[PDB]
Image (cartoon, rainbow, N blue to C red; front, top):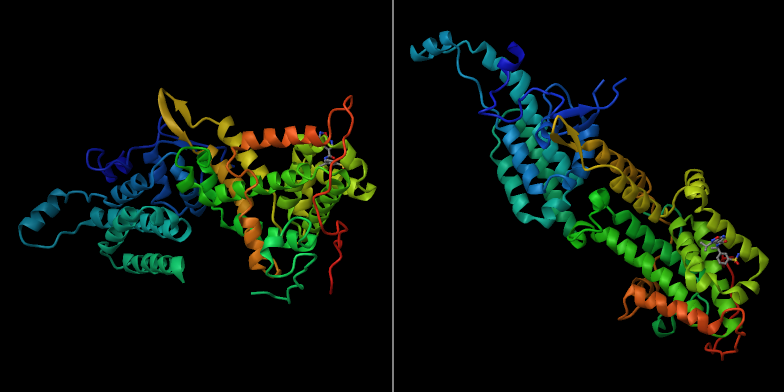
Length: 472
Ligand SMILES: CC(C)c1noc2ncc(C(=O)N[C@H](C)c3cccc(S(N)(=O)=O)c3)cc12
């Protein structure tokens, strides 16, 4: 048909083959059709489609493409997409040109206006969205940026002039931003036994429990806000190149592991029962202040520490914990029950700012990654399951909706550093350290037939807590 005769030949262009059941699949369209699956070539073709813009697809593709296409390959494919061959002149125009006259070129002008110009401006739109929202690809690969700048810098056109200026404007802004707010007054920085500057005395019981929760919420808010959606796609934080692909997410996971294991270590290394009860009671108060601040990440870090194998079994310790703190800690656990039903209800019904629980997102993304195939098979051909990537992108979109919520709390550089540099494991591996904590639990509180021995005190300061009510 004349429609495919107008589009370029396959031997001069790869992005003009007609759609079929063996190269592209769509979802139930009840409007722009939603792409379920397709070859990389049909994904690139639709990413820069001549008939219409598709901001939703551009956003999803640029967040998830690294799971099926390398950044160097994506740039090559969009540049190949941009270089559209022009058709030959008609017979009458060939005679007109050979006679020294100007051709009519009716179909060539139509093809340029209705196909070459829209596809080229759509490739430029991908380049703009790429540098605006995923500039880290260019920071991790300076050669990729050199190729991008050479490409946009050699583009020649009247409508493409403004596009090339907007892309350049963004690249330079990002480059400078690499190097170089409070609506209300923040509260007074709380102190308990440790004095400001006496970093040598900073510890779980010497610092004020309000200030521990405040600084940890500030630290976790910054860690939460730095994670980009692509660090979570394709489960790249669990693969070989995880350090370069997921640096902000791995930092968040290592903080959560260090804080949780540090709380466990504080409890089980406090061998005197009366003192351990004080330690557990102080961590419950830290959780109470995390609840006040809507830091569900920290609340669930305390729930993980108390539910751990070494701590949960400490029946003699929790026996002396006041009934009200027992109830708070039990209700906090219930946040996780029934696939985090109460947690999700609390997150939606809360007023900002908040530090959501990050573990649930990682769990749900791993469920989506493992429970959906990388490709779909149609007529013996393999198509990239794009709906799989879209579903992971929707979960990361839920993460992004809470990343613009700064807290009105004053940073205390020394307390911040104390929590950034927590190393409970030391030179031990996680399995070695958790076995140590469990054997330590059995030492301080042996199994029921064996009795409870008495251990000496290790703290030369008052164990009484100053509480969770602030000083204003
Ligand atoms: C996963 C574990 C194995 C588990 N299995 O069934 C449960 N039912 C409830 C609770 C519970 O409430 N967890 C909180 C954080 C908690 C921890 C330690 C002491 C206390 S408490 N109430 O003694 O202060 C509370 C935990 C579990």
